[PDB]
Image (tube, rainbow over all chains, first blue to last red; front, side, top):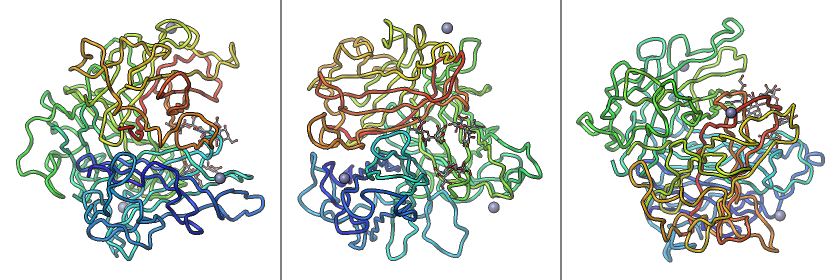
Length: 183
Length: 185
Length: 183
Ligand SMILES: CC(=O)N[C@H]1[C@H]([C@H](O)[C@H](O)CO)O[C@@](OC[C@H]2O[C@@H](O)[C@H](O)[C@@H](O)[C@H]2O)(C(=O)O)C[C@@H]1O
Ligand SMILES: CC(=O)N[C@H]1[C@H]([C@H](O)[C@H](O)CO)O[C@@](O[C@@H]2[C@@H](O)[C@H](O)O[C@H](CO)[C@@H]2O)(C(=O)O)C[C@@H]1O
Ligand SMILES: CC(=O)N[C@H]1[C@H]([C@H](O)[C@H](O)CO)O[C@@](O[C@@H]2[C@@H](O)[C@H](O)O[C@H](CO)[C@@H]2O)(C(=O)O)C[C@@H]1O
Ligand SMILES: [Zn+2]
Ligand SMILES: [Zn+2]
Ligand SMILES: [Zn+2]
């Protein structure tokens, strides 16, 4: 129960533009009050698989959202599929879907839901990853905690780039970050 | 201090003094993962000289420092910029009710990061990161964290915030950054 | 056995271009399914000790390799010397070489060895460190998992820079990252 993850294989588990067009590899490891997170993305098909901004000047970003209920269970309207998001067992998952993962949720006092109170930037982490592992192909991964509506907690990953990439496949290096846990 | 968390609490009540009393909330979370401490930090400035940055009217205002000084037992000293009242081991979204007396396992390692001396000062006692003001991607600032370089204490963690862009009336409140350091014990 | 490391003093323990020309400080802490890593480097002598790209325009990168066998034991072709890598015991290392550390190896499903199949970028993490701690002296540390031959697992650090440095001592700030563990 110390690690929630997508499993480390490369089987598509995420829908960005079309069904199962990407494998989001996400590992959440609970280190007490902080969750240590490691993430990467491989797009395998669809609109975001091969980026060509000469042809499509406007395709410059996309978002992957993980929505969770009060028990920390993933809601089906998340881009990530519920099928293989579970507690780890070896290189796979436990046989049964979990019913509670509140200790992996982002803290609501640190990262409040939208309200009419002042919105602070501490609920965002910025990182840079590299497409195809090439140092001159950076893309920004912006992670935001608890800013989606229709859920009790949320983790969203926005990927964007500013260079005019020509036939660059969207598959990334890995990024680590952490966040304060709800409990 | 097996896997405990030493923190500032996650609320937004000012707990730090940069230029004037209680002008900011430093949110700092230190979690012990054996020989390394996993740290998560962000800063909200609410008043004073560093609250709203205008480098067109004040081009020389480009950096400031927040210092956490600790004694031989890992206890935070009162002359640190961070206040002592809400820096303690975590209990729910708050702190345990007794001030801690020992936290040596959360201190930066003295062999990895020696106190100042006339021996060579190696760069490994610094970690650099970039955070963003207001969560805007076009508003970077550098957070430089240095271990054990202050005097008047046994251990120290110093945060230096600086920026090179010429900001015009930009509120200094930041995104979060994670780093780790080698623990003393 | 929760931390494998190099002792964080300044005694040389690594051979880049000549014997014991550097001190790699590496700490690997097992946080369950993820290893939390912290690395820095001091070059004390030889070719990479003082960088002068006016004198040597093409000296712009070097690599430090850690190669491990099936039991997670460091192999002698690694740049890091075997006498310097062991589980922590206070501020030093245990007195006898360890026999197993498979739980510290980079996961082979997440990071496969080279083969005929498509190679994904998720087996790389990029970071930037700073020479002499100066903010205007960045160098890239690229860390790759399980891409070397002659071993069962590997962690390799490639240090490179794009600026023309003139008489700059190669000793760095520290970088943290994590990776998915084998067991
Ligand atoms: C710690 C850090 O982030 N260092 C940066 C560094 C500093 O921001 C700068 O030296 C502070 O004055 O900048 C580096 O890039 C320089 C580069 O920055 C671009 O944004 C700008 O468009 C260029 O004109 C040029 O200034 C540097 O090498 O000094 C990068 C380094 O990582
Ligand atoms: C992994 C990394 O930090 N990548 C950098 C990248 C590399 O440092 C560089 O390409 C060598 O591999 O540099 C990036 O920035 C570039 C500058 O170094 C260069 O001076 O100017 C470029 C544009 O003219 C560019 O800005 C890059 O290639 O995009 C930034 C990237 O994070
Ligand atoms: C979150 C992050 O990486 N932010 C970058 C920022 C963004 O990449 C960019 O604003 C998105 O469009 O870019 C910064 O640097 C800019 C350069 O990428 C650009 O080519 O030139 C700009 C000046 O005209 C600027 O230098 C930025 O906006 O400051 C750097 C920042 O870290
Ligand atoms: Zn593809
Ligand atoms: Zn304000
Ligand atoms: Zn010398």
